[PDB]
Image (cartoon, coloured by chain):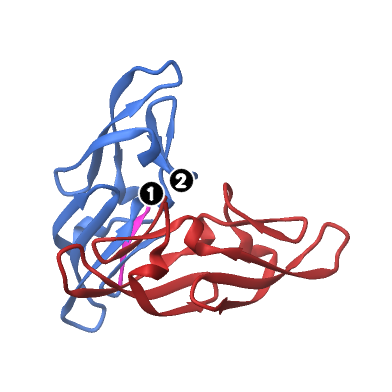
Chain colours: A blue, B red
Amino acid sequence: LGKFSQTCYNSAIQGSVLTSTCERTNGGYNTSSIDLNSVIAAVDGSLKWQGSNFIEACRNTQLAGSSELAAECKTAAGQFVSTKINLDDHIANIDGTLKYE
Amino acid sequence: LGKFSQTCYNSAIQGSVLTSTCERTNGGYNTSSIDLNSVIAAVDGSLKWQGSNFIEACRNTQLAGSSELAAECKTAAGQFVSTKINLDDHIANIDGTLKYE
């Protein structure tokens, strides 16, 4: 599942939104964006799938490398930790558009 | 929070996917989509935030007005009931991309 980074380039993250330019199935490419806040949660400071609204607990989001979302997130106790998640786990390039799967 | 309908137009709902054309922060427009199935649940026939996968229990999804999602969802007892939820509560436009917050 996922693996968008293998067929996309010029990816960027601003806030909770990922943008990238991806290869289409029958040739050519397309630029699209997807909000990651709908599909990533913060759980005691760690980014996890199967949830939403990590941005309520996190700040300074960045794209590290070709597919990692990095951020500083608030733990249950209230202090922050550095955390990351590999977007290639579930963000795919479906015919030129970024999708969660 | 939310209020995407104030800066977007030509919105449409297909299944659980909302598509709309939104103005970017400094001008210009972008058409994007967000899969509402990631952020809306259906509990005993009623659509609600703070959950996911409402489409598993619902049919006949439609956009009502500029910002409401309407559908028919299955109650625990078995029968379907009409239900609606206002997407403007938690779907926003950030620089041309639909986002959950």
Going by the image, does B31 lie left or right of B49?
Answer: left
Q: Residue at x 35, y 51 (%)?
A: A36
Residue at the right extreme?
Answer: B77
Q: Residue at x 40, y 75 (%)?
A: B19
Q: Residue at x 20, y 58 (%)?
A: A6
Specify start and end residues of the magenta stretch as a single range.
A90-94
Residue B45 image offset from top left, x and y in percent? 75, 61
SS class, disc 2: loop
Q: Is residue A42 above or below residue A37?
A: above
Question: Quarter-wise, where is residue A3 in the image?
Answer: bottom left
Question: Quarter-wise, where is residue B53 in the image?
Answer: bottom right
> Disc 2 residue type?
Ser
The majority secondary structure of the magenta stretch comes to strand
Camera-side residue of B68 and A9: B68
Q: Chain of mark 1?
A: A
Residue at the left extreme?
Answer: A10
Residue B21 image offset from top left, x and y in percent? 32, 76
